[PDB]
Amino acid sequence: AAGPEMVRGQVFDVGPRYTNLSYIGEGAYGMVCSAYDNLNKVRVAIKKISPFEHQTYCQRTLREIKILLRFRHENIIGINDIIRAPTIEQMKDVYIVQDLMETDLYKLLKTQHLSNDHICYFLYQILRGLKYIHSANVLHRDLKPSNLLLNTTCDLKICDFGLARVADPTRWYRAPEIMLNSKGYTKSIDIWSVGCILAEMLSNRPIFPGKHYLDQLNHILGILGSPSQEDLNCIINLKARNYLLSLPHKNKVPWNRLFPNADSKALDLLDKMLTFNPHKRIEVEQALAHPYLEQYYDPSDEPIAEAPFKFDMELDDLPKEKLKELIFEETARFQP
Ligand SMILES: */C1=C/C(=O)[C@@H](O)[C@@H](O)C[C@H]2O[C@@H]2c2cc(OC)cc(O)c2C(=O)O[C@@H](C)C1
Image 1 (spheres, rainbow, N blue to C red):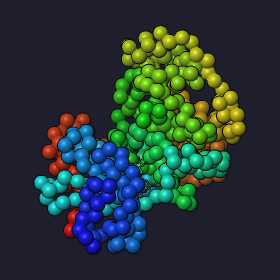
Image 2 (cartoon, helix red, strand yellow):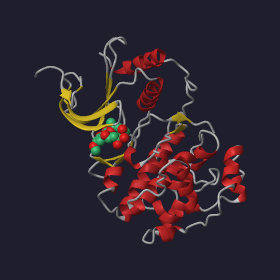
Image 3 (cartoon, rainbow, N blue to C red):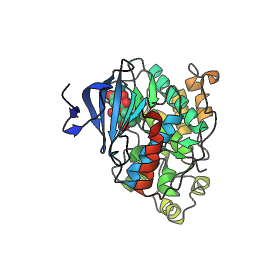
Image 4 (cartoon, rainbow, N blue to C red):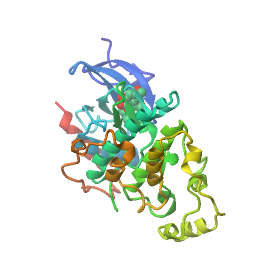
C-alpha cells in the first residue's frame, strides 16, 4: 500500500508490521500515533523520537529505553518493540512501540469527577508501580497526571521515564527540596509528586500551580505554611535557607478547608505525602499500608525488582555520537 506512511507531514516509517496510522500527540521531538500491530494482531501506541542532535535528548532516550526494557510490572508502560535503521549512520529516528492505552489522568481530570473508590484505586496503582520503581533503586522524577495512562478498565500505567535516574540518596509536581538545595536526589521527590496528584484527584485542580519559578515555592508555603525550625535545618544550602527566612510568615491551611468533601483518611495520607521536610515524608511501602488504601493493599501482590540498578553510565558527559552508539546497541535486542 503506497510507500512509507505519512502522519501530519512527518515521516512515520514503521515498516509493514504496523499499519493504519492515526495521530495522537506531539511532545516536541516525539510524535505519538496509534497503529495496528499486524504481528500481534493488537493496536499499539508508537512514539517517534529524533534525539540524535542533542546530548540531552539522547540521554533521555537512552535512559528511558534502558530502564523500560528491564522493567516488568503491570503499572508501568512496557516496550513491545523498538524500530530503527540497520546502520547507525541511517539511524536518524527511533520508534518506540507500547500498549495503546485509552486516556491519561490529565485528560480524565479535565472532564470527570473521580469517585472516592476511583481516587483510591488510581492512588493505589500509582503507589504500586512506584514501589516497584523504587525497589529497582530508580527515581521517576517527573510524576504528573499526563504521565499516568489509563485504559477503559481503570488499569493505570506509569509512563515517560526520560527523566529517570538511579537514586543518589512540569514545575507543578516538583518537591520543594529541588527548588531549595541540591538537584533533589531522594525517593521522597516522587512521593511529593504523588501527593500533588492525590490533591489533584480530590479537586480536579492542580494544588500548586506556580506561574513562575519562585511562585511555585509560594504556592507550597501558602498551603503548608512557613517551614518549622527543624524543617529549616534540612535546607542546608546557604542562599535557600536565607531566602526562606526572608519570607513573611505563613499559616498552615488545614486540609479539610481545601478539600471539604474528601475522605479524611485520604487527607491524612495527603498530609504525609506533602510534607516539606523530605525525611519526614511518607515512603512508598508505608503509603501503600495506610488506612486510606485498605481495600486494595495486598503486599503479596506488589512485586519488587529482583535486583536494584546502579547505573553503568551515570554522570554521562558523553558526546551525542557516543550516546547514539549505546542507543543503537540497546535497541539491537529488537533487530532482525
Ligand atoms: C507515555 C509518556 C508520555 O509521553 C505522556 O506525556 C503522554 O501523556 C503522551 C500521550 O500520547 C500518549 C498516549 C496517548 C493515548 O491516548 C490518550 C494512548 C496511549 O497509549 C499513549 C501512550 O502510550 O504514550 C506513550 C507513547 C508515552
